Amino acid sequence: ARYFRR
Amino acid sequence: MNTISILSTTDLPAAWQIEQRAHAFPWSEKTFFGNQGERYLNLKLTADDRMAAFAITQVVLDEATLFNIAVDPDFQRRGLGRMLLEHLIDELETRGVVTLWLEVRASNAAAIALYESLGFNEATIRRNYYPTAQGHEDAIIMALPISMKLH
Ligand SMILES: CC(C)(COP(=O)(O)OP(=O)(O)OC[C@H]1O[C@@H](n2cnc3c(N)ncnc32)[C@H](O)[C@@H]1OP(=O)(O)O)[C@@H](O)C(=O)NCCC(=O)NCCS
């Protein structure tokens, strides 16, 4: 899982 | 029976449910519904009736990043995760992709062991990349080389 600030 | 197919518009509400059930810190709805379209090779695994898993991947040039994989809790530890991952890898090889990349919580012993057994290696670590219920967790950045086959 990539983490987004979005 | 298990059936891996493309993840399309109609499939997204079911997958969004899976996203919120399988991740302690899921994406936001907008981010989730935004990771579709151009350059996405998104897959689902269907067990009989139900959607059991999904994977979000983006392909740029001859590398890919698996942004997300999720097996619904009801369907875990039954080999569906690996199976879906295996289908994706075959599919990327036919597409000329030579490296699959991903990020994983450093404490996800399950996911890491799966990836390791599929041939992933740790490339680099990003400290404090993930939030936790009590601070931050390290991210392990892992690369899987995909050998080219005859077609
Ligand atoms: C991790 C995940 C994607 C795959 O799980 P799955 O479909 O249950 O995995 P499989 O049944 O294909 O196999 C899991 C492999 O992980 C490793 N593993 C070690 N301990 C494990 C455990 N307690 N549970 C699951 N896997 C474990 C093994 O190599 C295992 O293969 P095995 O059958 O030879 O033991 C799924 O559990 C999930 O969605 N988890 C929550 C979300 C998540 O963490 N996603 C990945 C973020 S990087």
Image: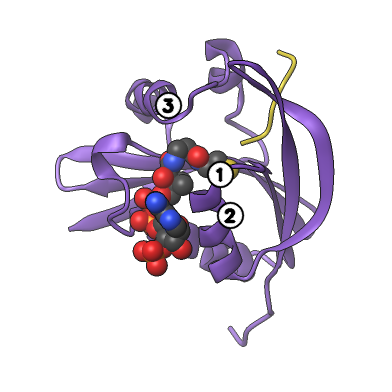
Chain colours: A yellow, B purple
For the view shown, which residue lies furthest in the bottom direction? B150
Q: Residue at x 73, y 47 (%)?
A: B140
Q: How many marks?
A: 3
* Residue B139 occupies quadrant: top right
Q: Check disc 1 and give the amino acid type.
A: Asn
Disc ID at residue B112: 2
Tag nearer the camera, 2 or 3: 2
Q: Residue at x 64, y 64 (%)?
A: B95
User: x, y percentage for residue B110?
Assistant: 48, 51
Q: Which structural element holds mark 1?
A: loop
Q: Check disc 2 and give the amino acid type.
A: Ile
User: x, y percentage for residue B100?
Assistant: 69, 58
Q: Check disc 3 and give the amino acid type.
A: Thr
Q: Which residue is mark 1?
A: B108
Letter of the chain that mark 1 sits on in the rendering: B
Judge whether B103 appears above or below B130 on screen.
Answer: below
Horizontal side of residue B92 vs B145, given as left or right: left
Q: Is the CB of mark 1 within 8 Å of ligand 1?
A: yes
Rendered-image quadrant of the C terminus of chain B: bottom right
Q: Is the CB of mark 2 within 8 Å of ligand 1?
A: yes
Judge whether B72 appears above or below B43 on screen.
Answer: above
- How much space separates mark 1 and mark 2, taking CA atoms? 6 Å
